[PDB]
Amino acid sequence: NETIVQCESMTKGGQYTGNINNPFGGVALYGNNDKVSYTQYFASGTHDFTLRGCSNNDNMARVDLKIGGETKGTFYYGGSSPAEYTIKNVNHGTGNQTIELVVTADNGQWDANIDYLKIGGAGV
Ligand SMILES: [Ca+2]
Ligand SMILES: [Ca+2]
């Protein structure tokens, strides 16, 4: 009923997307359009999405959730300590869907560190 996809296993995109080791094994998104994405098979259309990550500092980091090219919501991190952020009851298509995690709100004040994406609901 839950599946976890490590961000470091996803396909990198953008200018500077890179791997990090601390505060967890994961990926850093440093600027706008820095992203990771992968193909998620879905047998049904409604899931909760939880991203574990954090800012690199005390400023608020944000990561956008995209599915099938549609922006479905934004994960927010109010500091540098690793935390989960859940976006509940996201509707989306079935079959193979491209899940994208992308920075769009960078302004030179923070980087987004992302550990894993957890998807909850009706068969992991
Ligand atoms: Ca940045
Ligand atoms: Ca990870």
Image (tube, helix red, strand yellow):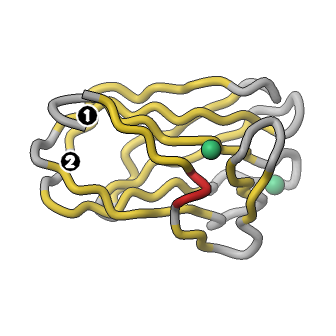
Ligand 1 quadrant in view: bottom right
At x 62%, y 32%, the residue is 76
- Quadrant location of the N terminus in the rendered image: top left
Q: Nearer the viewer, mark 1 or mark 2?
A: 1
Q: Which mark is residue 106?
A: none
At x 71%, y 66%, the residue is 17
Q: Secondary structure at mark 2?
A: loop
The residue wearing badge 1 is: 47
- Quadrant location of the C terminus in the rendered image: top left
**Position of 47 compared to 122: left or right?**
right
**Position of 51 compared to 17: left or right?**
left
Asked if labels 2 and 1 touch by Cβ distance under 8 angstroms, the answer is: yes
Residue 22 is situated, as x and y percent measured from the top left of the image, at 83, 41
Residue 66 is situated, as x and y percent measured from the top left of the image, at 40, 54
- To which quarter of the image does residue 41 belong? bottom left
Residue 33 is situated, as x and y percent measured from the top left of the image, at 62, 67
Residue type beneath disc 1 = His
Residue 99 drawn above or below residue 90: below
The residue wearing badge 2 is: 92
Q: Nearer the viewer, residue 94 or 91?
A: 94
Residue 8 drawn above or below residue 46: below
Residue type beneath disc 2 = His
At x 26%, y 61%, the residue is 97
**Position of 26 compared to 120: left or right?**
right
- To which quarter of the image does residue 90 belong? top left
**Position of 51 compared to 82: left or right?**
left
Q: Secondary structure at mark 1?
A: strand
Of the image marks 1 and 2, the number of the one nearer the N terminus? 1
- To which quarter of the image does residue 13 belong? bottom right
